[PDB]
Amino acid sequence: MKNYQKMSVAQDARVELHDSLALTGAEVSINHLPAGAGVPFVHSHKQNEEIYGILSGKGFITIDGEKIELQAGDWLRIAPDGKRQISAASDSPIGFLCIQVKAGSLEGYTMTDGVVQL
Amino acid sequence: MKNYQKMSVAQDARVELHDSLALTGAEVSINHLPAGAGVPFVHSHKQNEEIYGILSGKGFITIDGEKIELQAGDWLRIAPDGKRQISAASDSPIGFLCIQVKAGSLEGYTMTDGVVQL
Ligand SMILES: [Zn+2]
Ligand SMILES: [Zn+2]
Image (cartoon, rainbow over all chains, first blue to last red; front, side):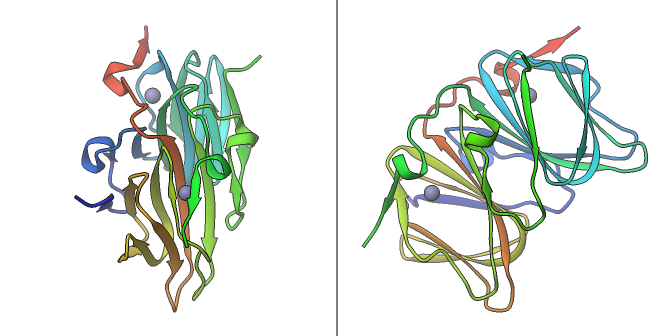
């Protein structure tokens, strides 16, 4: 079969890409919280590093008791042990990406993994 | 020390996050091409799976001779062997994310990797 899979996601749709795109190196979740709302729980990871990318709006994320302000354009790496909990701003919703990957699994990349054709 | 790292990226800035955020499970590149422009070369990967997310605009991506139309909200998985080359539309720029991760490296995730804190 094809060396790729594609799908379209609505502007304000909440979905996970792993099963729909048959990912093998990560899980990607697209989500967003309305103003004044936030993830109702705190969590960490056993072996997965997590990368957050704020696509729109603004808000906060509490990591190990410390709350960090967030706005569109902000990107964060969170180690497995980090206890996290994101939430939207009081006067604004927030849209973000959560890339889950096995910590320390990356080897070569770009220069050391890409192959130019002819 | 801290269990996280943060940085801000300008709306139209082109950067790679691996070194700046000290990622260990992936490389994330944020890029965008002006109307009528495109990556000047074709490439594949030795062992990294690649996930593309179109954040804005529209364009095309040619994978193994087949060109696929792209627009904001589109997400794709590309296997290592896939020969790819993205470009913007003739009448519009395109902004996208390229998540590079080692293919088949993901094990548990979400339900099988997240840990809720009481
Ligand atoms: Zn690549
Ligand atoms: Zn998580």
